[PDB]
Length: 53
Length: 478
Image (cartoon, rainbow over all chains, first blue to last red; front, top):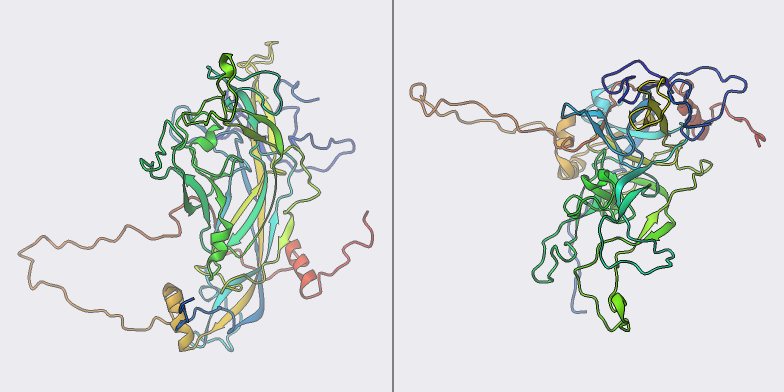
């Protein structure tokens, strides 16, 4: 699940949860397995970048 | 005993496939991708408008897909060669289905910042309070791990507890327990699942109405009433089901709140203190669903629905499919936040403002074997009694009268007038099928014939035509 373009429903804004938009791409060598919050980028989605390891 | 019945029946309600012959025509279909991405804990409405901003999408909610189908008569005929609208009429039998559910892991999860709890009663080192204030705390829980699936062809009826007639005769009223009356009514999409605290409305049954999570507070929770749905000798409310669920005791808690109902006082030796009184009794399990086991599932497996129970044995009636899925096992919840600024080195409630979403994936694939039903006049006689509107919709067994005259009276109220006429008042309302909330699924145009391009086609052949072409692969893969 990637970082999405802003929608009406959910937008990339403070006070508002970002949209999750599906990005399919080839499995890299050393790409991580799920967390238990699934498959997503966390680089961009987690602005604080201190929620997960 | 004297002298009953002995029975005179004398007309008998029959099985619907003993004159039904199958056809080797196969149509395939399947959906593009079912996806809904919502909020798991609660719905979010817009703060300046009535409507939703993010709906509630959790796997602890009933996901009811209302599948509306045409008839084969209203659709393709390959070849005409034994088919006369006279001799027979054609009907869909969906002989294989795939329920797709491959997505990442997460859990269904609900919670309430005002969840009731007195003390812990799994084990306690002290004596609980007789009454007190503000004994409620932010606790969250899943309701239980719930997998179920059932497939039918008429809307499906759940049970729930409603607020019955408060008695003055049994003295069941508020200030004592409310009345409970078991009411069957149809389950919906976004209807709540059973909470491990009974499947019941908690809107009028809970007068505190902050005892439990808010999502169930406003909604009716239902349990699929299996025993009534298979009691029906037609068997079209459902004709397949299975389930898997897990609930163990995470810990006993006691609900704060003391009863205003009698307690016998010969059941304990009075003490001294307030131990010459009994404290709160209203103990509850807290549900558990800790261990996810994604090795075992009732999903990602086709459902080969070649026949049905009841008088029905693989004929869609009403030309409908109702499929109810609850799945809490792989239902991903995701975590992210939006920053107010990354310059601020805090991590306040109004800085990086945390959030959680839920992403829910399903997919439905079909394969439909064609069938025909031979109609003789006596067969028609039963089918009209079963539901005349089958014969109407096909438009054979309806040829005429009725009626269709008379009269228009007049002559003349032109001039005058009585008043004037008027004509003619045409709704409310069709449809009776859609009078309840559902994930609307139109299927009337996705019909195919391919079986080597869908993976669902290939697995179907592996059972059937034999064919596939298989291994697959095997031998040995562990």
